[PDB]
Image 1 (spheres, rainbow, N blue to C red):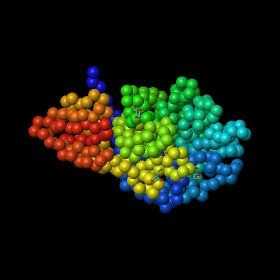
Image 2: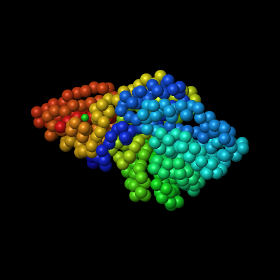
Image 3: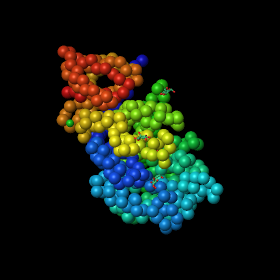
Image 4: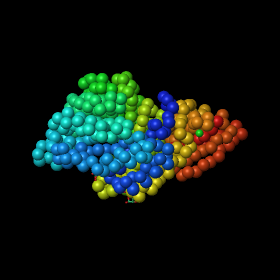
Length: 414
Ligand SMILES: OC[C@H]1O[C@H](O)[C@@H](O)[C@@H](O)[C@@H]1O
Ligand SMILES: OC[C@H]1O[C@H](O)[C@@H](O)[C@@H](O)[C@@H]1O
Ligand SMILES: OC[C@H]1O[C@H](O)[C@@H](O)[C@@H](O)[C@@H]1O
Ligand SMILES: OC[C@H]1O[C@H](O)[C@@H](O)[C@@H](O)[C@@H]1O
Ligand SMILES: [Cl-]
């Protein structure tokens, strides 16, 4: 046997349009988040996704805390960023939580119309915001207690969608990012259940958060990320969604102790993010958002502190430097293409071809078992390792010898 996963994107990818980042700007001073934005702009990116928690913005009924958010929205416009905000959680006055429950905000609102009016208020207050997203991961108990409720979420989404379109009928409404591939504890998927409730008629953007242990799946013997993504993306297109985003994905560089995610460190983070980026940019997403722009302080859980492209001082981590090298090699826009002709590409390889703006071909490739591959048609090419920054001219009188790594490499050829 011999199995290779080849991907070819369905359309051209323009990184500025396609690749955004999650951010947690309200956690930081304007001085600090403006530095983060400097680093983001240096990558040639402009899309950001920010979280709003209702119980932090409205601390009692009609008592708001918006000074920081007001300033942030002005600063985001001043930096020419394109933003999507999601609102999640119940304010204390409207929550369905039992009086004694420790997780008051993790319950949905008693009245979806009250939530909807808040989203409308925010949208009218901040017309520069590019898109509004309704709740977050409702297929997870931590965001919708005491148990997943597709009917309940559909009613919330419908009410919010109506209110948001009253404010601006042309602005996109984004449904909640579903955790993983939208699976619920009962064995159903939220996307399927919402489909039966006719939610696709609302015309909201569909999004999910396909975190996996490895870039290409959860186990080395079951690398089925591409299979799952293709399956859910096809179903969503079939349902007639206006667009598909992935509003969260990524890995933490935390040193532990282990909580869900294996310890991989700053170098593992760089490796995994680049491989996953190579996969998702060749799948049928209209936009994706890396989680996340910056490391966070002790207000975040141990794992959640280290997903950043940047450390707490807003300085590059290895994943940033790797992504920066990667995007410099690709240039700003990639058009779908085929990989070069190969001889003895190793079993397990991933293989993705593109052409960049100057017409040169770009081949993205890796394999868990490493090894070597021969390219019989080529006499010269340039090999890039975005993790080390090593650049190697390759040459041959009648074909190239190319080393294969477990990490992504980029071959630029003609
Ligand atoms: O709670 C974490 C952190 O994120 C929120 O968006 C803001 O309300 C901050 O003031 C808060 O400290
Ligand atoms: O907010 C990011 C959050 O995403 C999902 O809910 C999970 O994969 C967690 O692994 C992760 O921390
Ligand atoms: O099977 C792969 C997996 O197995 C072990 O538990 C650990 O070594 C992990 O770091 C590794 O990724
Ligand atoms: O937890 C992540 C955090 O750890 C330490 O505090 C420092 O190295 C920071 O720069 C880094 O962002
Ligand atoms: Cl170019």
